[PDB]
Length: 116
Length: 117
Image (cartoon, rainbow over all chains, first blue to last red; front, side, top):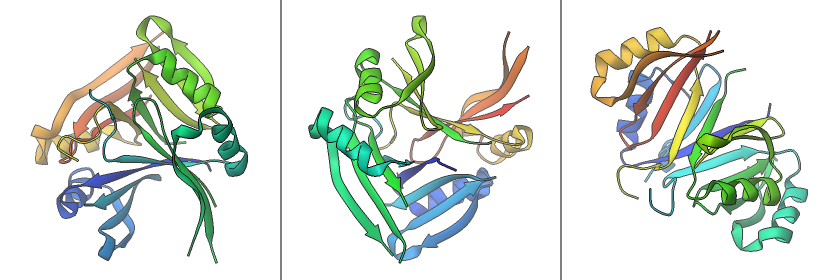
C-alpha cells in the first residue's frame, strides 16, 4: 500500500495535463484548480502535476514517499545528516492529518517522506 | 502490482548509496557493480541509483509499469511521435522479457514505460 508518488512541476499546466490525458491516456482522479494541481493515475499508478547533469539534479520533481515510521526516520536523519533536512517535520491537516518532512540528497533530489 | 520506480543518476554512486542506506535506512536489494547500478527499497517502495528551466527532471528516469504497452505506444506514435525518446523494444535476460519505450513530456520529464511478459 506504500508508494512513491512523483509530484511534477509544470510550466503550462493545461499543456501538461492534456499530454498526460490525451496522449498517454491517464485519468484525472481529482484537482485543485486554483492551485493548478492535478492528481492523475494510469491503472492505479499515480502522478501529481503542479503548475507554476548539473547540481541540483531532479529539478521540478518532488518525490512524495510513503513511510511506516515517520518519527523514527526523522530522528535517524537528524542524527546522521541534519543538514540534509530540507523541510522540518510537520503535521499537515485537512480531521485527516499527514506528518511529513523533506530531505535533499547529495545529488540534489528532493524527497517528501509522508505518513497519514 | 504496477508501480513507478524512479531511476536516479548519481555523481558518485558510492556516496549516494551510502546516503540512502546509512542516512535513510534503505536496503540494497541487488546491484550490477560494473554498471554502477543499485536497486534499493524502503519497506517495499523501490528506487534505482545509477552512477526551473526546460528540460526539467534532469537525471531522472521514471520506470513506469503499464498493463498493455502496445496500445499505449501506438497512440503516442500517432499523436506525438516527436516525443518518443526510445522506440518500443522487447528487452530480454536469461528467457524473461520486458517491452519498453521512453517518452519525454512537454516539460522535459523522461518516462520509461514497461510491460513484463
